[PDB]
Amino acid sequence: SSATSAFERMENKVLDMEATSQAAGELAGFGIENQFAQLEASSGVEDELAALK
Amino acid sequence: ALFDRLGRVVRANLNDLVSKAEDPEKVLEQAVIDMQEDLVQLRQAVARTIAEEK
Amino acid sequence: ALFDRLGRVVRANLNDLVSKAEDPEKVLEQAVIDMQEDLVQLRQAVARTIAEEKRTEQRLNQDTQEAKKWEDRAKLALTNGEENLAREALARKKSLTDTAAAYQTQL
Amino acid sequence: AQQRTMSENLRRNLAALEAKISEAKTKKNMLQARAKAAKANAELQQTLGGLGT
Image (cartoon, rainbow over all chains, first blue to last red; front, top):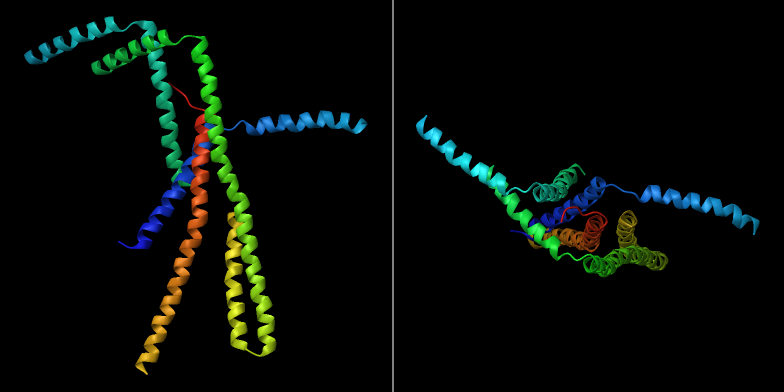
C-alpha cells in the first residue's frame, strides 16, 4: 500500500537477478583464465625478442 | 482379477504398436536432443537456488 | 509411460523432416550471419553497462567538489562571525562525504 | 507555547523524511546499473553456451 512497500520489493528483485546471472556463469564454467595465461606466456616469449631490438 | 486382466490387454496391444512406430535411429537422436534442453533448464534451476545462497 | 513413447515419436518424425529441409551450405552460411548480427547487439548492450563505469566516476567527482565549496563558504562564514551559518555549511559537507564514500564502493 | 513545540515536531519529522526520500533517490540511480549489468551477464552466458535445439 505504501511507496516504500513497493520500492523495497523492487530492490530485492534486482538483487535476485544479479545473483542468478552470476550463478549461471559459475555453473557454465569459464575458459577465460586459462586463455589469459596463454596470452601472458605468449608475451614473455616475445619480450626477449623485443629486448634485443 | 477379471477387469484387471482386460485392462492389461488394452495396454499391451498399445505397447506393441508404439514400439513398431519407434524407429531406432530417429528415436535415439530425438532423446539425446531432449536431454540437452532438459540439462540447460536444470542448470538454471540450480543457479536460482545458488542465487539465494549469495 | 505409453504417452511419452508416442510424444517422443511425433517429435522425432518432425525433427527428421526438419533435417531434410536443412541444406548444408545455406543453413551453415545463415548461421554465421545470425551470429554476426546478434554479437553486434550484445556489444551495444555491454557498452551501456561500461558507460556506468565512466558515469559513476563523474558523480563522485562532482559531489566531492560541492563538499569543497561548502568548506570555502564556511571559512568566510567563520571569519565574518556567524557560527550558525558556518555549522550548517560543515553539516552539509559531512553527508556529501558520506554520499561520496558510497559511490567509491559502488564504483 | 503549544504551537511552537508542535511546529518543531512537524518541522523535524519532515526533514527526516527528506533524508529518507533522498536515500531512495540515491539508491535508484545505481540500482538500475546493477539491473543492466545482471541482464548483460545473462546474454553472454547464453551466447557462449546454449545446448539442445
